[PDB]
Amino acid sequence: TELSERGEKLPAAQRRDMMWICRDGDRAKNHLLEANLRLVVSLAKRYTGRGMAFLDLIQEGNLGLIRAVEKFDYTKGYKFSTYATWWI
DNA sequence: CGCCCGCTTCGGGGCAACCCTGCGTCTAATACAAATCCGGCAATGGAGTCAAGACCAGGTTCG
């Protein structure tokens, strides 16, 4: 982003492997989301019985999980599920 | 003389359209910012109001 202005000229190998890292991060993000979808279902399974549909509850839990993997930190050394349960 | 192979015929399955043998309570807040109501003076400025007071015009009374 700070390179897209006239910050620096683009070397070929540096450009292509920084593109590889930038594309790899999104695949890792999607991998984490696709991992914890089951936790989302296991949390949403008990808020039924009033008003909304079960798939709607699951989808809003998915959106909360996207927010949780946005604002998740690992240097506190805790498991992901205890942090994401709150946001879901 | 026997034999394949699609054509027709019925069966069974599959599916589309209607009723009741149908018809649960759930963490719990804080922090903050923006929007909005609203309560109360604080400039009015135009619109209504009272009162005087003048304006003659033609009955009405008097000479």
Image: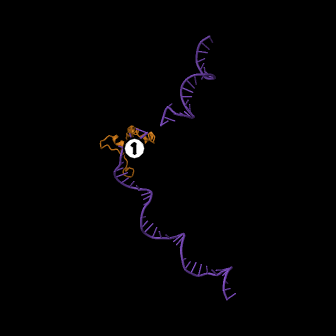
- Residue plotted at (39% across, 44% down): A64
Up the image or down, B35 lies above or below A59; here it is below
B8 up-or-down from B48: above or below = above
In-image side of B60 versus B15 (left or right)? right
Residue A61 coordinates in the image, percent (x, y): 41, 42
Which residue occupies the foreground of this view, A45 or B56? B56
Q: Secondary structure at mark 1?
A: helix
Looking at the picture, does residue B21 appear above or below residue B54? Answer: above
Quarter-of-image position of residue A44: top left
Residue A50 at x, y percent in the picture: 44, 41
Circle 1 sits on which residue?
A64
Instruction: For residue A64, say whether it is visible.
Output: yes
Name the kind of residue labelled 1 in the image: Gly
- Tell me if A35 is positioned left or right of B48 in this view: left
Within 10 Å of disc 1 (Cα), the crowding (few <14, some 14-19, many 20+) is some
Specify the chain shown as orange.
A
Does residue A16 appear in this view?
no
Asked whether B1 or B43 is in front, the reply is B43
Colour setup of the view: by chain
Kindly indicate the quadrant of the structure image that contains residue A67.
top left
Horizontally, is A27 left or right of B47 in the view? Answer: left
Chain ID for label 1? Answer: A
Residue B15: x and y, percent?
A: 55, 31
Q: Residue at x 33, y 41 (%)?
A: A82
Q: What colour has chain B?
A: purple
Residue found at x 43% / y 41%: A57
Q: Quadrant of residue A33?
A: top left
